[PDB]
Image (cartoon, coloured by chain):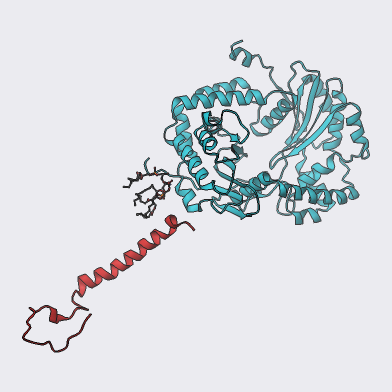
Chain colours: A red, B cyan
């Protein structure tokens, strides 16, 4: 089937759903996945309790 | 001799009406040859799912034998005096007409009176005609244009008797008992739904005398069709082995009434027609024709205005290779919207001249004149004089064409029918989106 008539609006819906989730995260639980320890000046004199990546 | 004088010099077609309801019409001008024909209001539009194809079978058996004239003797009487007998049965009309000499008019009616009223319907003739119809259905299967048009009718009038083909399904043709044929003749060959047209050198008084003497015994003094519906769809028969790709796209147009036919027939005349074997080609006024000739984008294209009583199909049918269907769709749709949005006066004048030539060229010769008389009496209820046609053409201008095209073309769901290597045919969503212009 041609891409324009169908697989544009479907991708539009997908991108809208992705935006729904993404603004839910941004606007209700901003620092959800991020570790709170980032909100602290980087002091090389103190190792954090647990060093973990994303 | 300034056209208008010639238009008013055309002899008029007097119309009379017998008690039975047969509408007798004649138009004598000079000729020693005449075309006399009975037009019935029967056809595939009236037959139900089981009677589909009965009209075709009746037309086939009409000439084979009658009651008064047993079998081939009928043909003898037609051949001995040089007359040419013919019959055609479209979806909503049937017609049996003979071309004969002016002298043979008294006989000419009689044979016709034998054919329409008292046929033979011999069982063995039915048995052989069944095989004849099956083979003819195969021939029509080989007819790619006719197959495409039948597909268009099926997909446009879906769920209505109009979608039924004239010949009927092959399964029906097998059963088709003689009782069904007799019933169909009884309830579809009645006197009120008959027009006895006669062109050429026939006197209306003589025609009335012969019709009264030969048609009085017919039924003197009920399913009468129903408004069909348009179902914008498409049927795609992907058959890649076929050489060319026949495509036909149509929209709901007007009927036999609804004078919008006159402007629309102008607009279609603007699009015109063209195939491989033509003249100027790239120099043709039609933008679609010029582009197709310049880029060799087609092997044929045509604009059709099939109009039934309650509705009709108005559109274009083109024949092109498998690698030019999409470009054809673009250009045809673009021409449609160009007419809808900005028609211009010069294009409308060209269309008016073309349509003026169409009617006068068509209404030449005894047979086309008689056919026009019958069709006009059945459909319009009257034979429209050429002067009235000229006036209706004159009243058409650019604004009227733009308005009617916007009414019938702009933003409408079309009915499409493709056959052959039609895989490049744009998806129905693309086709429908082509029927509205964002710029406008
Ligand atoms: C203003 C609103 C648009 C308007 O009035 O005219 C649009 C106008 C043309 O409208 P049109 O006369 O209906 O086009 C018919 C043509 O045959 C051109 O179209 P086509 O018949 O070749 O094919 C049908 C379809 C084919 O689709 C396209 O050509 C583009 C579809 C894009 C869909 C989104 C996903 C991809 C990005 O056309 C369109 O969708 C419309 C024309 C192209 C629009 C391009 C800009 C899209 C922005 C989103 O667009 C342009 O001239 C493009 C630039 C200006 C508009 C965008 C800014
Ligand atoms: C992108 C935003 C729109 C997404 C949904 C619509 C779409 O992708 O295409 C449809 C839109 C309207 O026009 P369309 O139906 O393509 O017909 C053009 C003339 N034949 O065509 C478009 O190009 C959409 C943007 C029109 C402005």
Query: Which residue is found at the position 35% from the left and 61% from the top?
Result: A12
Reply above or below: B66 against A44: above
Give the number of callouts. Answer: 0
Tell me residue A53's x, y (percent).
21, 82
Query: Which residue is found at the position 83% from the left and 51% from the top?
Result: B131
Relative depth, front residue between B317 and B63? B317
**Could one spot residue B345 in this view of the protein?**
yes
Locate residue B378 relative to residue B183 in the image: left or right.
left
Residue B344 sits in which quadrant? top left
- In the picture as drawn, the residue positioned furthest to the top comes out as B1
Tell me residue B335's x, y (percent).
48, 37
Tell me residue B421's x, y (percent).
60, 52
Relative depth, front residue between B70 and B380? B70
Reply above or below: B427 against B89: below
Tell me residue B110's x, y (percent).
87, 30
Reply above or below: A28 against B182: below
Specify the quadrant that holds the C terminus of chain A.
bottom left
């Amino acid at each position: 089937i041609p891409f324009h008539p169908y697989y544009t609006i479907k991708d539009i819906l997908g991108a809208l759903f992705m935006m729904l989730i993404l603004l839910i995260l941004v606007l209700f639980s901003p620092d959800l996945l991020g570790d709170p320890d980032n909100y602290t000046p980087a002091n090389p004199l103190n190792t954090p309790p647990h060093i973990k990546p994303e | 001799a300034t056209y208008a004088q010639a238009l008013q010099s055309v002899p008029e077609t007097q119309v009379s009406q017998l008690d039975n309801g047969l509408r007798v019409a004649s138009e004598q001008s000079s000729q020693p040859t005449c075309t006399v024909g009975v037009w019935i209001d029967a056809g595939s539009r009236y037959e139900n799912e089981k009677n589909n194809g009965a009209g075709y079978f009746v037309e086939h058996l009409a000439f084979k034998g009658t009651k008064n004239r047993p079998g081939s003797a009928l043909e003898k009487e037609v051949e001995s005096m040089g007359a040419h007998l013919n019959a055609y049965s479209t979806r909503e009309h049937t017609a049996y007409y003979i071309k004969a000499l002016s002298k043979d008019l008294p006989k000419a009616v009689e044979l016709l009176a034998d054919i329409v009223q008292n046929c033979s319907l011999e069982d063995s003739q039915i048995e052989k005609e069944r095989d004849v119809i099956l083979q003819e259905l195969q021939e029509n299967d080989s007819s790619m244009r006719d197959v495409v048009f039948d597909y268009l009718h099926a997909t446009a009038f879906q769920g209505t008797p109009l979608a039924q083909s004239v010949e009927g399904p092959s399964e029906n043709v097998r059963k088709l008992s003689r009782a069904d044929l007799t019933e169909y003749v009884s309830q579809h060959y009645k006197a009120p739904r008959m027009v006895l047209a006669a062109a050429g050198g026939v006197e209306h008084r003589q025609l009335l005398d012969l019709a009264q003497k030969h048609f009085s015994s017919l039924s003197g003094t009920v399913p009468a069709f129903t408004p069909c519906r348009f179902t914008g769809s498409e049927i795609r028969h992907r058959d890649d082995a076929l050489p060319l790709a026949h495509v036909a796209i149509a929209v709901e147009g007007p009927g036999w009434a609804n004078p919008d036919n006159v402007p629309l027939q102008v607009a279609n005349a603007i699009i015109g027609h063209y195939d491989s074997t033509y003249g100027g080609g790239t120099h043709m006024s039609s933008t679609l024709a010029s582009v197709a000739a310049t880029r060799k984008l087609c092997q044929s294209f045509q604009t059709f205005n099939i109009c039934y009583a309650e509705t009709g199909l108005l559109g274009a049918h083109f024949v092109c290779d498998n690698m030019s269907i999409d470009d054809m769709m673009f250009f045809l749709q673009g021409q449609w919207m160009r007419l809808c949005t900005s028609a211009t006066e010069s294009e409308v004048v060209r269309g008016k001249n073309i349509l003026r030539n169409a009617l006068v060229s068509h209404l030449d010769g005894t047979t086309p004149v008689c056919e026009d008389i019958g069709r006009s009496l059945l459909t319009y209820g009257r034979r429209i004089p050429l002067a009235e046609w000229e006036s209706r053409i004159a009243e058409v201008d650019a604004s009227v064409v733009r308005e009617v095209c916007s009414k019938y073309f702009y933003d409408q769901c079309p009915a499409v029918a493709g056959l052959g290597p039609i895989e490049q045919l744009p998806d129905y969503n693309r086709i429908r989106s082509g029927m509205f212009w964002l710029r406008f």
